[PDB]
Image (tube, rainbow, N blue to C red; front, top):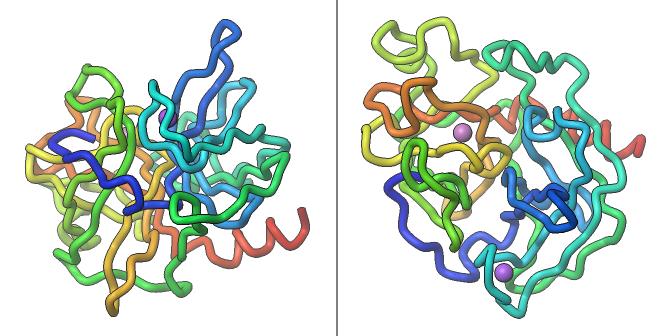
Length: 240
Ligand SMILES: [Ar]
Ligand code: NA
């Protein structure tokens, strides 16, 4: 997250760190949202590499004992069947991970609430992105979970030529594009949290930013629109 602030420890208890085995150690690669005690929602593109993955729930600092973490292996990966790794602009950037254990819920570990199917936020609706991604284009991962205030940019504006043009789809949410604050590499798969009728819901799965830079004016961060995939998600979990 570029231009973020450190989240307080209990703000976003559905946020997970998706990690892969590198050497014999684990490295953060992506975010995700806990949606069942044994299921995580992330970006399809996060789990293209044939890697060993684990999930950390209750994580705040990637490099320090928080005293709240639970570390759980990924047992099964279900990528959206229409996902195409060489075509992120086509959408379908979403995957579900079945965990090897069911995590214990507490103030640091809660299920993320998803929007009702078909819900589209009005232009300039207030949202936070969260994650441990780069804090500057071509920078380094955050140590502590970051948040940034990223208002939505509706499809009509986002798909305009000075924004993302034909790249963005109605199956996506755009947010930010102020040139200061954005998602960045390592935030992929994580949530966009938007406050509706007094409660946050996870409206986005972080998908992509511009090839020119993370925080580029009129290139808002682009997210898979969670409310497009409610049936898909439930179908996967009910068959798995
Ligand atoms: Ar990203
Ligand atoms: Na930690």
